[PDB]
Amino acid sequence: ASTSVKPIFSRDMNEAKRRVRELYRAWYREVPNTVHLFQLDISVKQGRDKVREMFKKNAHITDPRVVDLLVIKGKMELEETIKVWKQRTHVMRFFHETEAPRPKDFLSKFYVGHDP
Amino acid sequence: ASATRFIQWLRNWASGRDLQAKLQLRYQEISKRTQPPPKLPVGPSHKLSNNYYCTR
Amino acid sequence: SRGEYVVAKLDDLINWARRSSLWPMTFGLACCAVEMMHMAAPRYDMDRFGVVFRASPRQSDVMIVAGTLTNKMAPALRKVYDQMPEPRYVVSMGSCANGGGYYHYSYSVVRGCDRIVPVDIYVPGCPPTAEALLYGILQLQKKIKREKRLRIWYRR
Amino acid sequence: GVRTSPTGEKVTHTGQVYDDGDYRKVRFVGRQKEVNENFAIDLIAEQPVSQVGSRVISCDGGGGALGHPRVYINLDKETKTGTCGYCGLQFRQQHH
Amino acid sequence: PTVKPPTARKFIWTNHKFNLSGTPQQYVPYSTTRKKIQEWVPPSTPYK
Amino acid sequence: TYKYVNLREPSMDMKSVTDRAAQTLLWTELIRGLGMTLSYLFREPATINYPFEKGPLSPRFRGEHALRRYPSGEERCIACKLCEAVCPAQAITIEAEPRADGSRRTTRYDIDMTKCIYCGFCQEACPVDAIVEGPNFEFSTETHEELLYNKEKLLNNGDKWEAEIAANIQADYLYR
Amino acid sequence: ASKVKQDMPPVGGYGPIDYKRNLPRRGLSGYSMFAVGIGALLFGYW
Amino acid sequence: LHHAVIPHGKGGRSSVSGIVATVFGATGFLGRYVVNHLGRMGSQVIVPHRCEPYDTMHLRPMGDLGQIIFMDWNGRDKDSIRRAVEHSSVVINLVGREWETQNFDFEDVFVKIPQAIAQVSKEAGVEKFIHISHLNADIKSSSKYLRSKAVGEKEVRETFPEATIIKPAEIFGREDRFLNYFANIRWFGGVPLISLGKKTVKQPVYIVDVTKGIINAIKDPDARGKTFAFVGPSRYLLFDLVQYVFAVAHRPFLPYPLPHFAYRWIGRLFEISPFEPWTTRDKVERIHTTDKILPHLPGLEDLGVEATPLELKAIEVLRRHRTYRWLSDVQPAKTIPTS
Amino acid sequence: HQDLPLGLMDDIYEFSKNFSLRIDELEEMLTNNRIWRNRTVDIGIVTAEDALNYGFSGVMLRGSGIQWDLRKTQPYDVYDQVEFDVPIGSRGDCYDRYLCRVEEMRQSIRIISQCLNKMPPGEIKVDDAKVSPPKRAEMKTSMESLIHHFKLYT
Amino acid sequence: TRPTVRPRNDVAHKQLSAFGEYVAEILPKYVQQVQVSCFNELEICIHPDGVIPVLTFLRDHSNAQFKSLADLTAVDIPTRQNRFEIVYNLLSLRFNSRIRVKTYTDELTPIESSVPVYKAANWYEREIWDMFGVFFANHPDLRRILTDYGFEGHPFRKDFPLSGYVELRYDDEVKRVVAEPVELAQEFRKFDLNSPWEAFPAYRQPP
Ligand SMILES: NC(=O)C1=CN([C@@H]2O[C@H](COP(=O)(O)OP(=O)(O)OC[C@H]3O[C@@H](n4cnc5c(N)ncnc54)[C@H](OP(=O)(O)O)[C@@H]3O)[C@@H](O)[C@H]2O)C=CC1
Ligand code: SF4
Ligand code: SF4
Ligand code: SF4
Ligand SMILES: [Zn+2]
């Protein structure tokens, strides 16, 4: 049948959502010494808040194969921050400290330009 | 090529070979920098007959 | 008689020293590094202008960017520039290091090294011929000869 | 044949000149505005018109393969002059 | 040049200049075209 | 056909072994290396005295750009945009419109000498030999902006290098 | 109306070009060098 | 204004914002951030400089090709001022100096030069003008630095009636001369303080907050002909503030008192050097001046900016004063209640 | 793109005539040097099977003894009309692959010598204007040769 | 023979066609299609479930002995349901011949890693994952190889813009190299070069 599709790691959501939790634990117990080695100027508080935001955006997913990739890519993004392959700039590219706000209210977009 | 004979012998003895016949500097064996204009050939398709494109 | 003359001549000496002993740090990244090596070859012999072949970043004075500066490499280039002792100059060599060159529109290429470090000379070409680069280094010396570091101190 | 504007900015052959209050004039302060003195439209209108005795004359820019693609020009119209599309030289028919 | 002099023409420079970079005579780029869109100048005579 | 580069076995007779023993103990082979460098201490160096001497080139060389003119004075460029469509790096921007005398001529011609890869395709495609790569290679600048040529700079280069550009084409226009 | 003229090898071809390894052999036998060295010492000690 | 340069783009590096700005004194600590913001949004910034072209190199990467323009000027040549402001729409003056010189003193840099800029700008046609003053500015203060700003601040508003004036407090930052100053006193042993640092209340303000505030005044039309006062979120006691500096620096702290007159004596032999004075009699006074609490002047919040706490961005500045790289938390400095 | 300018194949002969000695001067410094041998002998040993299964090609196969060179097994152009030899290693280390490269410089002189003698006359680009552009003399006198010039470059 | 037409090689055409049926008969389970192009190349199309059985056959079978992985790459064709097209190019030194083996997958379907068969495929599969997003199962180490660290996307896919989504510079406020949305001084210019006249009647698709 066409609907049947080969899996990646998990055969259903219940098994797939286990890895999200195991991945989350790795990140939560890695920020404090990530902020230490990289000598960042962000507290462990808002560092952990950032990981909360990243997961929360991929919360509407319902496909076990899509979730596996988002975990596989999540594990890679962690191996770079533990083996310090990333430099100080790469870790600070999540926090967007150099892009001016882009307001969402209609008037602000109307005043500035033609975009929606 | 302006090396005195005694220096020629010393450089030749040190290297174990006659370096004067195979200088790595060019003096006069290079071709001239201005040449007569050429007239290059033309390919085998420059025919006025029996040259329909569909056969090549 | 005026102090301006005493400090103008004394500025010429320090300018002369810094222009007759340039010690470059070659950031050879791409093809443009081959022409840099030729400039050090017997025919041109940069070493006879007081310019040594290579040096460590903290013994260096001028940084020669010769190649394409990708995004992955940009963080490293800036770090070496920050650790170079002053005075320091950057020579941007080749079309890739000036404004992107052949790869201007690539997702992975930094469209000009001037977006990462300041630049004092631009040597165009693809690659700039070994002699073209030697025109850039000499043109760099004439910049250092015009500097008035001590004059501006005397009139603050 | 420059036509320097009242504010003192030269006009190029394309006709570009910044207006009195255009902030882009600041790029010239301390420097100069690159302008080409020899205008194309003033060097090709000062050429003599060639008189030829046939209804069709062919121009190839002069110099053989160092000019422009050879074209053929029709001189049947008495009112105006034939004009090469590439080089701008002019031709006229003798009497007919 | 003393033997084979170049061909002479009116538009060729009679005073060759050297690299003018860094001096006031340097070259400053600019757009050589004209304005594309023209705006509407309101009448200077007040209404009413 | 092939050949072995390092297949010969060393000898094992009394004289051969002593030669290898004498070489090791007396540094014979290394003293032979010092000889070669000594020869180069008595050879004329190949260094040319730039800038009073120059490296050889040929008429085909590809350097700074220049828009040419006809013998009369009219521009050769008729704004066909063939060069713009062959430029690998998209370093050329062209705009055109009828002139006051009703001729096809350009009102914008810029070469971004930082995007350009100095490849020569622009002069291979020009049907009237208007855009050429002159023989100059010494135009290093002190600012990024002044490497963005427009029509005025290119036309000055034609009026500046016409003496040498025309000669080079005369020596090369039969091969191309 | 001249013939075709283009770059071609001269009539009769070019002269031979060497390419093989030609490292010369030089020096005295291993025995002899020791004899000079040993003999140099003994005169020194004497 | 029939030209009205029109914004285009997404407010990025290659966009057009329509602000043609002349930033006098842009080669210094406060200039770096103002030029950086103006260029980061694609603005035409003219940078007149008195220094050598080498010292302005760090500014070149801060704008797109052709945006940052450098001109040569002299504070005593009004024609050089006019050449740098005739084509602009906003003029920002950041000229100043912590010490006097044989050629320029506090009267010339804070009154004569600012007065010249305003008079030239008004005739040139500039519609905006941003001036920078000091929060503790008055004409009855022992410090000469703070006396010359009060005089100048008044002359600007009688020469450019629409000018905007800003009165920040001691600004801290990476290149500042406030936090780095205290950390550098470790060379001479103890850390002398008039009295013992008590009775001194200071309200430092972060550089970016000042920089973001200045830009806002260039966009909104409510900032014309109005005075502001950029101050931090909390008020500290000078002793507590200095103690916190050595805590982050993780260095010995041995404060000892020094009479006010005695502190001025040493400040006289430190200003005899023909170079950047290490400390001056004037510097001692400002370090021990209690920042005013003017409540009738709009602050950063009135311009949409939010003040940055000292604690959040203090490890950033002092990181290099520590003598070990990692060092394996420092308690926040005591804050006076706002009341 | 263009034919060789007159007076070029003579200069190549002058360069090729003297190059072989330059290689000999290179080998004097390195081949039999004890210091250079110690930094390349028994270093980077690669087995024949590993070289093939790791995707190695070129002197990385020959250096290990595998007899393979695309110029002789899958010839392209006229590499089937030049005689040359393919140096082959016996040990598969840095020193052997250094001798293959130094030997390959000598076989290149061997090939370059033959190319100078056996160079035939004629044209230098396919005589088909729909693939290779026409000459500028023809593009300026024939309407067919201008259309094909126009469309090959646009 | 014509001087401007590449000569045919009928002898090679027959031999590779003969070897095409040989493989199709020995692996009916995986082989789906077998071509031989007019310039004598052999392409074998297989079900994705047959990467190891068909590669292990060619690498070990006596009459195949394809003991060298020339290259491994993917081709993106968005229109197809399974957009990606994995391609293997093998070489046989014993028989002096080359064979190209093609399979396919989509975004979310794994393809078995071939490192057990060809150690050269280690890095090649990392490149496919980095540039195309295809995930290879049981790969000893699967990480980005070419792209910048933390790069979001897969550039070689046909729907990733040529200029990317972010660009780098050095903002002096924070003293680091930062990333910002992409803005270009001169937009890349799109050319419509395709002629509206059929160029080759031989490759004409059905209506
Ligand atoms: N930073 C702080 O803590 C405070 C700042 N301010 C005010 O901000 C302004 C200065 O800020 P800041 O950046 O730290 O000062 P800086 O020490 O960093 O330099 C000020 C700039 O003004 C120039 N300058 C000084 N004198 C002259 C002169 N005679 N002629 C021309 N230029 C001159 C300097 O040019 P160059 O160096 O190249 O010679 C320099 O670029 C002052 O008005 C100050 O009162 C307000 C409250 C606190
Ligand atoms: S500018 Fe040209 S030679 Fe230099 S790195 Fe780029 S492509 Fe290579
Ligand atoms: S040389 Fe090449 S890259 Fe440069 S302008 Fe001409 S066609 Fe474009
Ligand atoms: S330079 Fe030549 S090819 Fe380019 S537009 Fe002008 S005429 Fe056409
Ligand atoms: Zn014509």
Image (cartoon, coloured by chain):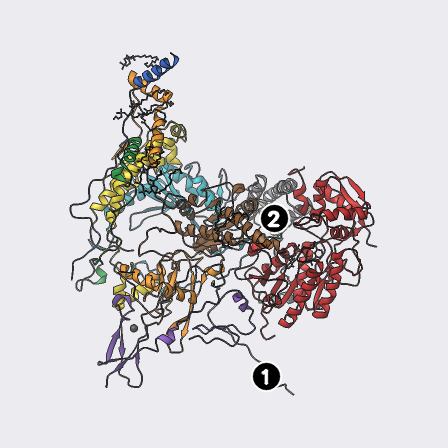
Chain colours: B green, C brown, D purple, F orange, G blue, H red, I yellow, J cyan
- Local SS, label 2: loop
Amino acid type of the residue that numbered disc 2 sits on in the rendered structure:
Met
Quadrant of ligand 4: it is bottom left
Q: Nearer the viewer, residue B20 or I57?
A: B20
Eyeballing the image, is F87 above or below I88?
Answer: below
Q: Position of residue H114 (x, y in %)?
A: 68, 64
Q: Position of residue H28 (x, y in %)?
A: 63, 55
Q: Quadrant of the N terminus of chain G?
A: bottom left
Q: Which residue is mark 1?
A: E43
Q: Quadrant of the C terminus of chain G?
A: top left
Q: Is residue J94 visible?
A: no
Circle 2 residues within 10 Å: few <14, some 14–19, many ≥20:
some
| Whole-number angstrom distance, CA of label 2 to CA of label 1 | 56 Å
Q: Which residue is mark 2?
A: A92
Q: Nearer the viewer, residue B11 or D79?
A: B11
Q: Quadrant of residue H218?
A: bottom right
Eyeballing the image, is J175 above or below D37?
Answer: above
Amino acid type of the residue that numbered disc 1 sits on in the rendered structure:
Pro
Q: Say left or right for I76 vs H52.
A: left
Chain under label 1?
E
